[PDB]
Amino acid sequence: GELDLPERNLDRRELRDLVNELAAHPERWAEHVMFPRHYASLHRDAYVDVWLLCWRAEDDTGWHDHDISSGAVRVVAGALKECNPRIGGEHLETVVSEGESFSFGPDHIHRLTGAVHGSVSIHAYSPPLWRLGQYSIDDSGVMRRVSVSYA
Amino acid sequence: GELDLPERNLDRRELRDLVNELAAHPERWAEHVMFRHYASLHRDAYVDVWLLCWRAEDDTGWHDHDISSGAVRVVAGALKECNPRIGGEHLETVVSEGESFSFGPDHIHRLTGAVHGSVSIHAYSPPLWRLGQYSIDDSGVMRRVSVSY
Ligand SMILES: [Fe+3]
Ligand SMILES: [Fe+3]
Ligand SMILES: [Mg+2]
């Protein structure tokens, strides 16, 4: 079935424990490994959403926030680049490789890209990722944020 | 006070029309000028309309309006509207008395540098239930705090 999680929101630390423990339980996700993006929902209810992501080298989230959702990421196989925006334009880039995880609160703005072909990652959000902010730049250079429904 | 409007969220052109219409009807807002101090002119399921009196120190900070379109009419004085540019050389526009502007729901801006005693009318649709307020670390990494209002 779906995952058997608490009936409440999880904080950042709890979300990071969740994605790491799921990674140690391939019975919960191996079936859903599928390469195109391709994402597969492992769990979606009123408190938490969990997705399994299978990456191609070209895949790119764009710059986004998660509105009011905290989140965590565990890389199961391969490696991703987590990028954080800086107003100067010299953005911070970190490689996250197999075995590693990180979490963030709801104020986070980031971009995931640069994956090794075939990478696999588990992403959890609490409260659920029902809204995402997608940033874009005009030819002027002026930045905008489009709020998108993900429910 | 109730406003004769379509029973639906309004677009940015409709909101600009609204703020300019209200600016032409001082009988509706003149009583509420007070020196941002703010007075609600009308709030319902579809729109929020505010009168704002500015001091020279007032500053919204950088923010978005989540899913709300908006419009501003400067009734007296002047405001600076600024729009952020990657690179740090932000676009700045002085909006003087008599002038108005509107924007869709993707806008990021900051209002500040008001002549002392400026008066403006602001309308949002859908209502401004949530705002995103941007901040930096001393590292320089930008964050967005979602504020319920
Ligand atoms: Fe994300
Ligand atoms: Fe605003
Ligand atoms: Mg165990």
Image: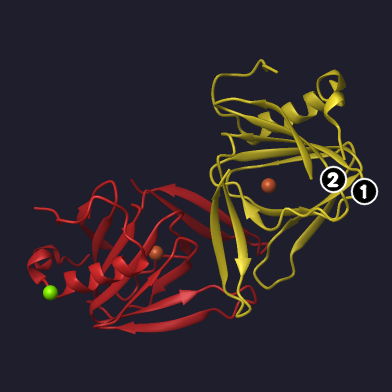
Chain colours: A red, B yellow
Q: Is residue B124 above or below residue A108?
A: above
Sooner in the amino-acid sequence: mark 2 or mark 1: 2
Query: In the depicted view, which residue is nearer to us: A119 or A21?
Result: A21
Q: Which three-letter amino acid code belongs to the residue tagged 1?
A: His
Residue holding disc 2: B54
Query: In the depicted view, which residue is nearer to us: B103 or A99?
Result: A99
* Number of marks in picture: 2
| Badge 1: residue crowd in 10 Å (few <14, some 14–19, many ≥20) | some
Quadrant observed for ligand 3 in the rendered image: bottom left
Q: Which three-letter amino acid code belongs to the residue tagged 2?
A: Trp
- Find residue B40 and report its image quarter: top right
Residue holding disc 1: B116
Chain designation of label 2: B
- Find residue B84 and report its image quarter: bottom right
At horizontal 7% and vertical 67% (from top left) the residue drawn is: A27
At horizontal 19% and vertical 67% (from top left) the residue drawn is: A35
